[PDB]
Amino acid sequence: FKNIDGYFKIYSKHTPINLERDLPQGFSALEPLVDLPIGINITRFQTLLA
Amino acid sequence: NFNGLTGTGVLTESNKKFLPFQQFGRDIADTTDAVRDPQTLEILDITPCS
């Protein structure tokens, strides 16, 4: 997630893993999905749990 | 003029395979020589005018 002037530039990438210990070693590109033109000051974030 | 991309040249059928999110394209010298049609998914090589 970024804080560009007007856009947010949501990036994402889904890759299968097998180590299951920590962040697996390897290089994978992050393809953009949507660029929402949301111009607002963002200085605090919090995720949601189910 | 493809969404602000203004220039001159000939549009020829290219054999490149652009990514599902990439429309523009530049060479090593930062010169636009390939772009897809934003209306119909089809790559178009931009060769300079004679």
Image (cartoon, rainbow, N blue to C red):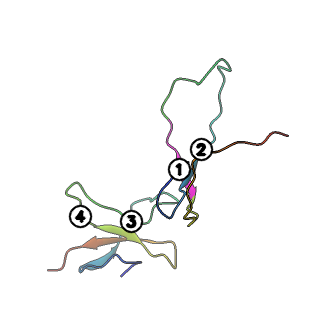
Is B10 situated left or right of B4 in this image?
Answer: left
Amino acid at circle 2: Lys
Spatial CA span between label 2 and label 3: 21 Å
Callout 3: SS: loop
Contact (Cβ within 8 Å) of mark 1 with mark 2:
yes
Report the span colored magenta: A28-33
> Residue A45's spot in the image, x, y percent?
65, 45
> Residue B35's spot in the image, x, y percent?
38, 69
Amino acid at circle 4: Thr
Mark 1: give few (<14), some (14-19) or many (20+) Cα within 10 Å: some
Callout 4: SS: loop
Query: The numbered mark 1 sits on a residue in which chain?
Result: A
- Residue sitting at 45 percent across and 76 percent down? B37
Callout 2: SS: loop
Q: Which residue is mark 3?
A: B24
Is B8 situated left or right of A4 in this image?
Answer: left
Relative to B4, residue A7 above or below: above
User: Which quarter of the figure has residue A21?
Assistant: top right
The one nearer the camera, B3 or B44, is: B3
Q: Which residue is mark 4?
A: B31
Q: Which residue is mark 2?
A: A13
Query: The numbered mark 2 sits on a residue in which chain?
Result: A
Query: The numbered mark 3 sits on a residue in which chain?
Result: B
